[PDB]
Length: 204
Length: 204
Ligand SMILES: CCCCCCCc1cc(=O)c2ccccc2[nH]1
Ligand SMILES: CCCCCCCc1cc(=O)c2ccccc2[nH]1
Image (cartoon, rainbow over all chains, first blue to last red; front, side):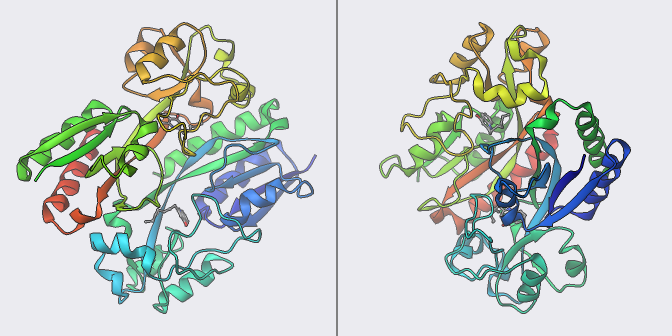
């Protein structure tokens, strides 16, 4: 009995180490699959992907063949080159973010949800977060990326934060867990959440 | 110069005491207005309401004449009569919540956002949270209400919680602050957030 799991690129590696660790105690065949958060909800809807669990930040409660629950929380920031014109982080900057270029991720389906849809009118899409930060480091525009994708570049001064005025301490983001309805009965999955969650709580 | 503020019924009174307290230090005319969270985003869009600040949990970033920011967090639960059939709180209960009657709030505009839209197909609307809990205490159905609306009834056993399986510790919910673009310049508003937030942080 194989178990195909989905972890988007927005899941920090700490979360990743916790998921894989537990599943191996009861399940003996686990397939980890990485996807862009814009393509997470899309790939699980595919009838042929046969995805059994998915751990993404994207929001969509009414999904067929799937339930929803929360695993933990994680921070994300609005980054930009330290010399970007909007570097002032002013209240007018938070509002005029929709007037400058944003570097959001591209959806293989061309569709974005309310959470991940680009907020700005001038947008430039990319494939993964790696390609985003490169363009952001070059002052091309601003974007929203996880904390672990940016923790290093900030201490090096390579990037600057602008969301503090919007949400201090970073944009707390929910990490949902979509699980096939067939697993709601098997107690092996029950033990997974109680363990995966209790460990993520120890992080903070 | 009058200042019309909007606090939905989902804002716990602790949040309410903090908002009113600060505004009186710099502003000398403040009008507090309460609304149903389903009618919060709707009343600010009214050209005649002339609302200057709004503090609600409802999500809608692309609003004309308004910006957005986060003030704090608050918990909400899925409540039900302790003898409700779904009292088991099982994984099948969290999924079958869409099959039983829900007691959600009614929108004066008839429209609900992604956050507040009733998740279940069998729905029964009400005007405020007071009318919800009454019906919930009578085993009519389940609903989602703030923590301060339910903190008393739980210790009395009058209600039971079901969201622990979905999100332990309660459904952490963001409390946004919509402020008119005209206030982004006045430093009086700047001092409000830095004060309103720093105090809400002391709560937890
Ligand atoms: C000031 C910005 C508005 C608030 C952000 C909107 C929600 C949101 C949009 C994102 O692309 C994103 C990307 C990675 C992690 C979380 C994210 N969350
Ligand atoms: C298992 C339930 C799904 C998650 C809840 C959906 C979001 C949500 C829906 C609500 O009506 C609500 C009411 C008051 C405070 C917060 C709320 N939040």
